[PDB]
Image (cartoon, coloured by chain):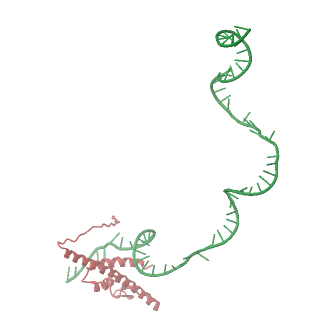
DNA sequence: GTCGTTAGTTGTGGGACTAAAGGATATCGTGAACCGAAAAATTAGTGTAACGGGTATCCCACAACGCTAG
């Protein structure tokens, strides 16, 4: 069956449901920290998904090697030790865990790794 | 005999002359010379290119997951 839906987005205002000011402020500061960690994360993922392609290019300029993004346990020419999205998610979680939730990391990882493969041509 | 009055001319001046349509004209004669006025035309003079961050907008492409284990 075809897609019988069209994606849509709505803006819902939310207040923090706490009695006192200090708890609300603690939650709001935690969420601002979440913002900062998310942006630093996005930077880390994009750098870490740039570098390896240029390592591929380096090897190809060395001996025309056909190195490709795949787990070496599943590919002879693979260099990665796991799935690429897992590599970015790991290299961001190992540093930013315990401060902001990991679902933000997973969503950001998917959102950037999906687009970067399309941007490979450019 | 003479002077004002009245009526009847007599000459002279001012005012009329359907309605409807249409509706073209041609218009001489010559004396000079200098000064002033304003309206017009010609001429003389000055010139950019990219750059730093930071941020307002545009076009243009893509995303907006699903499953398993502690």
Residue at 39% across / 84% down in the picture? Answer: A50
Q: Which chain is green?
A: B
Which of the 4 image quarters holds residue B44?
bottom right
Front one among A111 and B49: B49
Examine the rendered structure and indicate whether residue B64 appears above or below residue A85.
above
The quadrant the N terminus of chain A occupies is bottom left
Residue at 39% across / 79% down in the picture? Answer: A116
Front one among B4 and B42: B4
Which of the 4 image quarters holds residue B48?
bottom right
Front one among A21 and B28: B28
Question: What colour denotes chain A?
Answer: red
In the image, farthest residue toward the bottom: A62
Q: How many marks?
A: 0
Q: Is residue A117 left or right of residue B65?
A: right
Residue A78 coordinates in the image, percent (x, y): 38, 87
Residue at 33% across / 77% down in the picture? Answer: A110
Examine the rendered structure and indicate whether residue A86 appears above or below residue B17.
below
Q: Is residue A65 left or right of residue A30?
A: right
Residue A58 coordinates in the image, percent (x, y): 44, 89
Q: Is residue A15 left or right of residue A113?
A: left
Residue A79 coordinates in the image, percent (x, y): 37, 88
In the image, farthest residue toward the left: A19
Residue at 30% across / 85% down in the picture? Answer: A90
Examine the rendered structure and indicate whether residue A1 appears above or below residue B5.
below
The quadrant the C terminus of chain A occupies is bottom left
Residue B51 coordinates in the image, percent (x, y): 48, 81
Front one among A94 and B45: B45
């Amino acid at each position: 069956m075809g897609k019988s839906t069209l994606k849509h987005t709505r803006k819902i205002q939310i207040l923090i449901d706490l009695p006192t000011k200090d708890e609300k402020k603690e939650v709001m500061d935690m969420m601002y920290q979440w913002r900062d960690r998310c942006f630093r994360a996005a930077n880390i993922i994009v750098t870490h998904l740039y570098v390896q392609e240029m390592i591929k290019d380096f090897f190809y300029l060395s001996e025309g090697i056909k190195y490709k993004l795949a787990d070496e346990k599943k590919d002879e020419k693979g260099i990665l030790q796991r799935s690429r999205m897992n590599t970015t998610y790991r290299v961001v979680s190992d540093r930013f865990k315990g401060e902001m939730p990991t679902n933000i990391l997973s969503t950001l990882n998917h959102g950037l790794i999906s687009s970067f493969n399309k941007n490979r041509v450019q």
